[PDB]
Amino acid sequence: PKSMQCKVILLDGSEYTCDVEKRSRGQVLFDKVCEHLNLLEKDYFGLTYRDAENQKNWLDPAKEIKKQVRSGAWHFSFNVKFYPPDPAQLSEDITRYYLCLQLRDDIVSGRLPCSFVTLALLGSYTVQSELGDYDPDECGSDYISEFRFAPNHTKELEDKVIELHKSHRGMTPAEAEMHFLENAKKLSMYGVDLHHAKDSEGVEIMLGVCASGLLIYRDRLRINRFAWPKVLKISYKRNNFYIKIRPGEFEQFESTIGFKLPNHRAAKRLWKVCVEHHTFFRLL
Ligand SMILES: CC(=O)N[C@H]1CNc2ccccc2C1
């Protein structure tokens, strides 16, 4: 029985290596990673892999690994797939912990934009969770944390992290992680998967996929939002992605909004992430 070596980048930046039978479905490798992580609330998470153009793709747990990675290396990342709108509802602290690690990467990467004060407040909870109570002995007036807090670090941000860290004395890691999530969950780009697209007139937009629905970012004055209930049907054809928007009460016909994606694969990817969010958040 021939087995392939899999390498998984974990959310703490460490590598997990295992073997699966070469005809294995994605669920087989995912179950192994989740057992390694002691993760029970697995529904929020998945494995990603990068293709030739270094684009992210979700490993479909129902399909053969080999038919997805195809010509590529069996190299994956462990990631949050469905960001819970209310992380307090999750049953386990260890679930909230992995969600925190994902969000820390969302912030440092700049996928999740954040004000100065929110960067410092999130960083202060991470430090409280990881080092415990503030200790002056470690930090002088010139202190810079090993922790990455932001896409661009400044001495002013490092100082503000410490000032807020002083206020969290006696906070346990679980408690600091819950405060982290209560702040992060309110950010306008929390849990938003962004896709480059063009509208029916060729104007560059972004489409955002999240728990609540689909967002169309046209300009800073113009953001269209379609709550999942308002979306009757999703489709792709060639490089195009279409959504069928319910008629208002007393209207005869649904409206259709079409978008141009860069290529056929980018249209299919957007379609599948929309279908998965629609199913998940319809049941949650
Ligand atoms: C205050 C607000 O606009 N809340 C939700 C409502 N609806 C909605 C629909 C699609 C994507 C995101 C959202 C955010």
Image: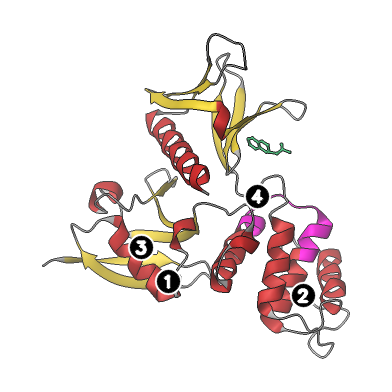
Q: Is residue 160 above or below residue 54?
A: below
Image quadrant of residue 146? Answer: bottom right
Indicate the position of residue 275 as horizontal and vertical percent values. 44, 37
Residue linked to disc 1? 15
Asked if disc 3 is less than 8 Å from ligand 1, the answer is: no
The residue nearer to you, when weighing 169 against 104, is 169
Residue 150, can we see it?
no
Q: Decide which of 91, 65 is in the foreground and name it.
A: 91
46 left or right of 88 in image? left
Marking on residue 190: 4
Q: Which residue is under mark 3?
A: 30
- 3D distance between C-alphas at marks 4 and 2: 27 Å
Query: What residue would you read off at disc 2?
Result: 144
Q: Give the percent coordinates (x, y) of residue 196.
A: 55, 33
Amino acid type, callout 2: Ile
Circle 3 — which element?
helix
Task: Please name which of the two marks, 2 or 1, marks the residue nearer to the observer.
Answer: 1
Using the numbered discs, state the Cα–Cα distance from disc 2 to disc 3 in whole angstroms.
36 Å
Instruction: Give the structural element (helix, strand or loop) at label 4.
Output: loop
Residue 268 visible, this orientation: yes
Q: Amino acid at mark 1?
A: Glu
Q: Nearer the viewer, mark 2 or mark 3?
A: 3
The 10 Å Cα crowd at callout 4, few under 14, some 14 to 19, many 20 or more, is: many
Q: CA distance from mark 4 to mark 3?
A: 24 Å
Q: Looking at the magenta stretch, what is its main secondary structure?
A: helix
Q: Is residue 110 left or right of residue 27?
A: right
Amino acid type of disc 3? Answer: Phe
Whether label 4 touches label 3, CB < 8 Å: no
Instruction: Determine crowd level at label 1: few under 14, some 14-19, many 20+ residues with C-alpha closer than 10 A.
Output: some
